[PDB]
Amino acid sequence: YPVFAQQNYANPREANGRIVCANCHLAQKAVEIEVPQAVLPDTVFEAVIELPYDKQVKQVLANGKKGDLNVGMVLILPEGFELAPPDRVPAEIKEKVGNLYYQPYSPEQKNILVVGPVPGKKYSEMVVPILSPDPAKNKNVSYLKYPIYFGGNRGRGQVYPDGKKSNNTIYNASAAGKIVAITALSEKKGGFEVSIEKANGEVVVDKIPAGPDLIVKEGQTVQADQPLTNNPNVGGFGQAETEIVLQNPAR
Amino acid sequence: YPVFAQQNYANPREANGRIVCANCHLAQKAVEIEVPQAVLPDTVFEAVIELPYDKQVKQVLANGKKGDLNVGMVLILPEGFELAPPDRVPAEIKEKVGNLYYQPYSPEQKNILVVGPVPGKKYSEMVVPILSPDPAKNKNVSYLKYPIYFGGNRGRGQVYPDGKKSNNTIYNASAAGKIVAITALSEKKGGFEVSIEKANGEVVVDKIPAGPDLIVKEGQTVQADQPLTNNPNVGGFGQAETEIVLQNPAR
Amino acid sequence: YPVFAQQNYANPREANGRIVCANCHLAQKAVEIEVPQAVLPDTVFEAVIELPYDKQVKQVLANGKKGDLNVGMVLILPEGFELAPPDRVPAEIKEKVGNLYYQPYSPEQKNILVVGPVPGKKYSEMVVPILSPDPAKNKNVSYLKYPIYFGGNRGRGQVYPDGKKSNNTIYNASAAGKIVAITALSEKKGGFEVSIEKANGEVVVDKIPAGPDLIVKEGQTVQADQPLTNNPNVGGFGQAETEIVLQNPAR
Ligand code: HEM
Ligand code: HEM
Ligand code: HEM
C-alpha cells in the first residue's frame, strides 16, 4: 500500500524516475494525469488522475477468494506545491474530490501526496486539489515550467515488505526433478504442495498458496525456477509525467 | 494495543480484508479461527482462536530486556452477533474462556470484539462465547451463511500512533556518512548513540534504544537509512477468516 | 522575465553587446530609448523608452489561450548613475513614470535597472527618472561621454532557464517518419500528441502543448526536426544603444 512505500522508502521516486510502487507491483498498466498547463501563484487547481481497468474482472484476495480491486497513488509535485487546505477548496471541487483523504508522504514532504487503498469501483478516477506556491514568499520556488510525477496502482502486489511473495504472483520450482506428488493444502485453506524428486533422489516440497492455478502435472519433470503456476495477477502499476507553469502575474 | 486501533481507526477492517493492526505490527504470523459450521438463533457458540508461536523465544521488552510476549486480537462478527452475556454462558464454557474480558470495539459496534494485551503463555489459544442473533426479532439479520473475520497478534509493535518507532524494530542511519563514534546511550541500561559524519563535515548522532543489536562498527561507512541494527522482532500479526450458518429451525 | 536574467546572468550584457534576454526571446523587435545628449552633475533627467507592438494582436498564453502582452526591460547606465530617489523626482515626472517599480539588477548594480513584467497595454512607453552622479564626490566617474545600453521586451519567451521550451514557440518532429496518429493532449484544454512511425516500425509520440497550431496532418510524412506547428510568437526583444555627456559646469 502507499503505507508500504512510506515505511520502506524515504523517496518514492528512484534516480531513473521509477516510482517505488513498482518494486512490488510488478505488472505494468497505463495511468493518466492532467493538470492545467499553467496556474497563478497561491492558486488552487485540480489534478485529475485516471487508473482505468476492467471492473468486471476480479482479483485474488489475501484470503484466497476473488474480489474487487482497490486503488492508490503517489503524486510527486514541485517543491512548494501542497495539498490545498480545506479552507481553500471550493465546495464544487470538494464535491469532485469526494470522501478522499490525501496525505503527505511524510511531514517533511508536503509536496508528495498519497491516497489509498480506496475502492477502484468508485475511485478509478480521482481529483486532487493542489495549492500552488508563491515565488515571492518562497525562495525555493520560481516562475518555471515544473515537472509533475505520478504513480498509480490498482490491485494487490506480488511481494511484501519482508520479501515474501504474496499469493497474487507466479510460483516456481525450488529444484529440478520429477513431480512425484501434488497434494491439496486443505479443505478450507486452499493451496497445494508440489513434491519434486531431484535427480539424487531427495524430495523437496514446494508450498503454493490458493490463488494461482497450477500448470504442472504429477509425473511431470520440471526445471529449477520453472513456473509451476500461471500468473493470477490482474492489476498493475503505471506512471505518467506532466508539467505545469507557475505564472508570474503583474499589472 | 487493540486500543490503539480503537482510538485511531473507526473500522478495524479495510475493504480488501486487511485488519488495521497490520499498520504497526509489520511482521506476518499465521493465526487460526474455528467456529461450528452452523448455529441456531439466540444460541451461544464458541469461537476458538489460536495465536501460535514459540513460547521459548523471548522478545525485546520496552525496558530493553528480553521477556514474554502478550497477545491480542480483534474479531469482526456479522451485525446482530455479540459477546454472549455472562448469564447465557454455561459454567463449562466460562471455565474454558477463563479470565478474559472481551470488549466491543466501541459501544456502537458490539459485533466487533477485542481482547489484549494478555499473556501469550496462557492465552495463545482462546475461546470466545458468542450469542447468535434471532431473525424473528432482529430484522437486520437473516438465515444466511455469515463470514467471520479475525486478526490476532503476539509481540510488541514496531511503531506508535504518532509515528515514533518502538525499540522492537530496525534502526537505520538517519544520514549517509562514516561512523566516527559509537557510545552507550545508558551506562547501565544499554542502548547506543552512533555518530555519523555526513558527506559535508556535519556530524549527526543517532540514538538507538536498548533492545535491538548493533550491526555496525566505529569507523564504518553507511548509506542513508541503512540498517544499523538487526530486526529484534520475534512476534507477528496474522489474519484468518471463517463462516457460520445461521440456521432456521424447521417445524 | 527580467528576474530570469538576474538569477541566471551576473552581467546582463555579453562582450559582443548582446543582452541576455535574447538567449530566450528569440524574435528581434525594434525598441527605442532617448536620454538628453548631456546632463549636469547630480541632476535628475529622464530616459524615455518605447517598446512598440501591434496592441490589437494577442499572444499565446501559458494556459493555451490568447491574451495581452507584458513588457519588461533592462537599462545599463554608466557607473555612478542610478534610479532617482522619490524625493528627487518632480511630481511632473512621477506622473509620467506611472506606477512602475524600477529595481537594481542586483544590490551591487544600482546602475542597471529592470522593470516588468508589466502590461504592455499601459507601459509600451516608459519613463525612467535617472539621477546623474557627481564627479565632485564620486571620483570613479568623470565628465565624459558615457554609453547607455538598453534591452526591451514584450511577449512571452521561447525557452526557460532549464532549457525547456515554452508553448509560445515552434515545435518540431523528434524523428523522421509518418504521422500515424494525431490526438488531443487534453480533451478540453487543447494540445496535441503526434505519433510518428519511423522506418523501423518504432513509434514515438511528440506532445505539443495548447498554443501553437499544427501545420501537419495524419498520413503525412515528416523529417526529423521538421516543424509540426506554426510559430505562435508575436512578441519580441530589441536592443538600443545611446550616449550621454556628464557636463562640467563653469565655476
Ligand atoms: C506506493 C506509493 C504504493 C502504491 C501506489 C500501492 C498501492 C496499493 C494498493 C491500492 C493496494 C491494494 C490493492 C487492492 O486491489 O486491494 C496495495 C496492496 C499491496 N501492495 Fe502496494 N502500493 C505501493 C507500494 C507498495 C510497496 C513498496 C510494497 C511492498 C514493499 C507493496 C506491496 C503490496 C502488497 C503485497 C499488497 C497486497 C496486500 C494484500 O492484501 O495481500 N506496495 N498496494
Ligand atoms: C488491534 C486489534 C491490535 C492488536 C490485535 C494489537 C495487539 C497488541 C498487543 C497484544 C500488544 C502487546 C504485545 C506484547 O508482547 O507486549 C501490542 C503492543 C503494541 N502495539 Fe498493538 N495491536 C493492535 C493495533 C495496533 C496499532 C494500530 C498500533 C499503533 C498505532 C499498535 C502498536 C503497538 C506498539 C508500538 C506496541 C508496543 C507497546 C510497547 O510495549 O511499547 N498496535 N499490540
Ligand atoms: C531580461 C532582462 C529579460 C527581459 C526584459 C524579459 C522580459 C520578459 C517579460 C516582460 C515577460 C512576460 C511577457 C508576457 O507577455 O507575459 C517574459 C516572459 C518570459 N521570459 Fe523573459 N525576459 C528577460 C530574460 C529572459 C531570460 C534570460 C529567460 C530565460 C532564462 C527568459 C524567458 C522567458 C520565458 C520562457 C517567458 C515566458 C514565461 C511564461 O509566461 O510562460 N526571459 N520575459
Image (cartoon, coloured by chain):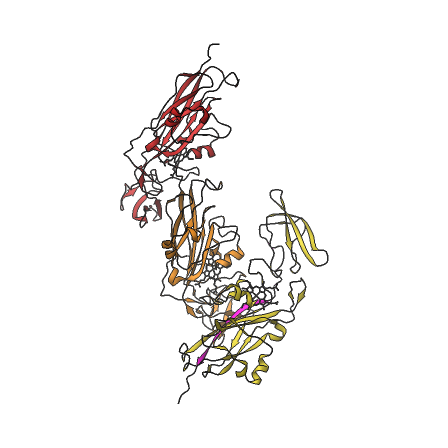
Chain colours: A orange, B yellow, C red
Tell me which residue sits at (39%, 16%) in the image: C37
Residue A18 visible, this orientation: no
Residue B61, above or below A131? below
Quarter residue A246 falls in? top left
- Residue B77 in percent (x, y) is at 48, 74
Camera-nearest residue between C227 and C84: C84
- Residue A247 in percent (x, y) is at 39, 41
Quarter residue C215 falls in? top left
Horizontally, is C244 left or right of A4 in the view? left
Most frequent secondary structure within the magenta stretch: loop
- Residue C41 in percent (x, y) is at 46, 17
- Residue B222 in percent (x, y) is at 61, 50
User: Which quadrant would the N terminus of chain C be assigned to in this image?
Assistant: top left
Q: Which quarter is ligand 2 in?
A: bottom right
Asked if the stretch drawn in magenta spans residue B163, the answer is: no
Q: Which residues are magenta?
A: B222-251
Tell me which residue sits at (45%, 74%) in the image: B79
Asked if the stretch drawn in magenta spans residue B223, the answer is: yes
Horizontally, is B173 left or right of C143 in the view? right
Camera-nearest residue between C242 and B53: C242
